Amino acid sequence: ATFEIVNRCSYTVWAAASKGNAALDAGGRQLNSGESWTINVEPGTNGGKIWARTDCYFDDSGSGICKTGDCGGLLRCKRFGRPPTTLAEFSLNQYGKDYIDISNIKGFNVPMDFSPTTRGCRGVRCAADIVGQCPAKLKAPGGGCNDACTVFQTSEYCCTTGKCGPTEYSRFFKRLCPDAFSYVLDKPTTVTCPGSSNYRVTFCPTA
């Protein structure tokens, strides 16, 4: 499946793509403002994610740091990124269908749209100014708006045992972005697409 990753932000981002234990495609790349990078994701990929990283520095070998979404210091991500990270999440060719969503469960750094480029389903979007509106206690000094699990490490926020409810913090994310997961047990906003759909992830869609 193809995923065109487009940076419409006025700032550079370093796109990342992983399924948690492996890179998807090259796993990451710099995207200056306006640039597009198309990756190929294998059919059947379960639990894939794409995200933006901000404020990165990499040496010639691709080792370095980012202020949001760092993945072990690698330009080329092999694992998931450090919160806060707005997440485009997908599982492909799952009994004939693809499933996509956006999640704020790991916080928010960059606004995104995640849409099919092929027919048969709608896209999802979280493009409100969550960083600007972020509750004081969730603001990450390194940049972005942390989720409450990251900040407070409680069973309730982290949904550790599977029984949690919405919270004042989750409700903030949900108010700003109704179409994204705000906590682990949120009413799902997953979209079912035809198996083997192709997609576009756009950072700063309303830039």
Image (cartoon, rainbow, N blue to C red):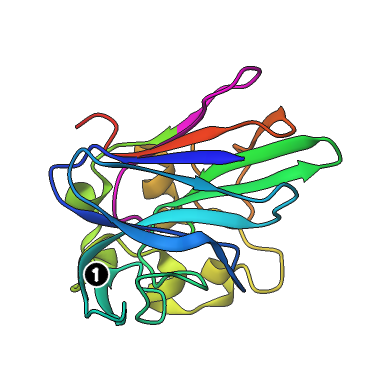
Residue farthest front in this picture: 60
Q: Residues within 10 Å of mark 1 (few under 14, many from 20)?
A: many
Visible in this render: residue 106? no
Can you give x and y, in whole percent of width and height, for residue 56 in the image?
21, 69
Please name the residue shown 34% across and 81% down the image.
73
Query: On the rendered image, what quadrant is the C terminus found in?
Result: top left
In this rendering, the answer to whether 128 lies above or below 31 is above
Nearest the viewer among 108 and 204 is: 204
Please name the residue shown 66% across and 18% down the image.
120
- Secondary structure that dominates the magenta span: loop
User: Which residues are drawn in magenta?
Assistant: 107-124
Q: Is residue 109 magenta?
A: yes
Residue farthest right in this picture: 95
Visible in this render: residue 27? yes
Please name the residue shown 62% across and 21% down the image.
121
Please name the residue shown 40% across and 62% down the image.
28
Residue type highlighted by circle 1: Ala
Residue farthest top in this picture: 119
In this rendering, the answer to whether 134 lies above or below 201 is below
Residue carrying label 1: 140
Can you give x and y, in whole percent of width and height, for residue 54 in the image?
23, 62
